[PDB]
Length: 79
Length: 80
Image 1 (spheres, chains in turn blue, brown):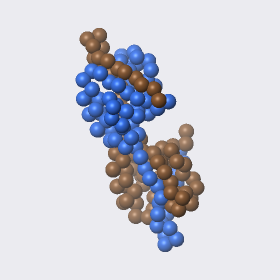
Image 2 (cartoon, chains in turn blue, green):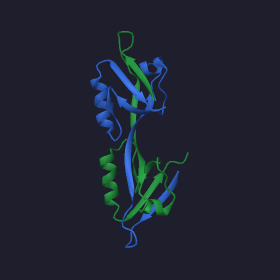
Image 3 (cartoon, helix red, strand yellow):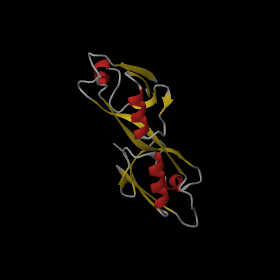
Image 4 (cartoon, chains in turn orange, cyan):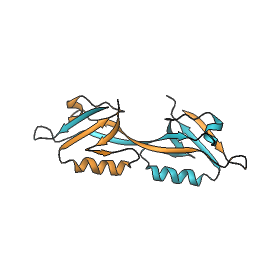
């Protein structure tokens, strides 16, 4: 970990920092289909869930898309 | 990019997939303090903003925390 401190003044009032969010694989259970399928890795960045892009999507909204899948979950994953 | 397809049946009804979200540095502008300070990198994962942990925080909420910093922004960033 490193700390970074940005401080405004009349020389520069702009942080000049654009943030995003990404959805990632936190854990795969030993007993689940994710593990049994064997393709997904913990820490993988999920790019799409069932056609819908996940960049900047909230975790809550991404979880809703998983509940919506109705037993068919097509993921696209960064590699 | 690779595709992964998980399919439920009576043999296994558990995806067994826990998701998280992380906040990351999308861009630093050429003219901004982030660039001028020189420590932050594009693609860095932000772990905390002014003491508040960012794992699983929405982008909207994280952005609110940057607006609340009032000209002093202390970040903790993943290097590990």
